[PDB]
Image (spheres, helix red, strand yellow):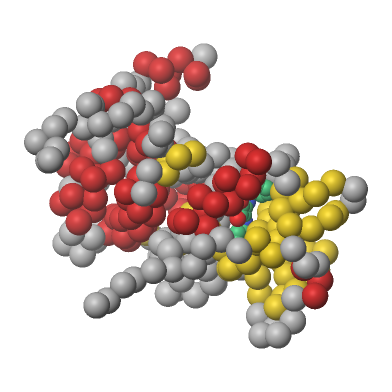
Length: 283
Ligand SMILES: C[C@@H](Nc1c(Nc2ccncc2)c(=O)c1=O)c1ccccc1
């Protein structure tokens, strides 16, 4: 008998200062709180600390992230503390310190020798299975943006990981013949992750977003303007087109995305160079 099982979420109640040295160095800012760099007193290694005000909404978002941490392409939660900061109660999330910078920053800070079509596909597949894992366990991320994609280290061997579960939500409430519609109700959710994914691929290839701009998005109108898109194949554009469907119910599912040849065969796509890096050094 073999029985694979992992630990549940243990919310530690003791002061974080017992276990960790807390710096005044920032690695992330938002409206909801801050992300600081911390060191483990015992092991002496680098970590990230996300501070949130302790409301039931946050406690669930942590539970979803903790549940998601088993995925190699999702930033892993290590410890969760509930402490008293100021007068208010608050949550303290301990994560693996990702100091490899933002995704587009590292593509731009290459001093580029050009950036290939193949390497962009490798990036996409990794973000793909990050979404695939989430969707497979009924979690929609709902905030997949360039800011929330960070690399582990400064290494050229670094792993890309998806952060920020401040918008993640649970998509759930003989017979192997029944339809998925009859199996309970579900809103849009997962589809918006797929849109974000399509957006990211566009910016990855050329170097600019595809998009009354709020109308041009709702129209689904975007050029593939040259001489950037003159090198990219019809197959790739058709994939972006499938990911950039206006209608959510028409937009490609994650399972279909990962099955697609360009994604599945990350090591078969032509190694044709892109102008991406040059384009980012403008705005
Ligand atoms: C922008 C975002 N930034 C975020 C992160 N940054 C990391 C940095 C280093 N290592 C791991 C993660 C997260 O995690 C995360 O969420 C943020 C959200 C809420 C509050 C403040 C900031």
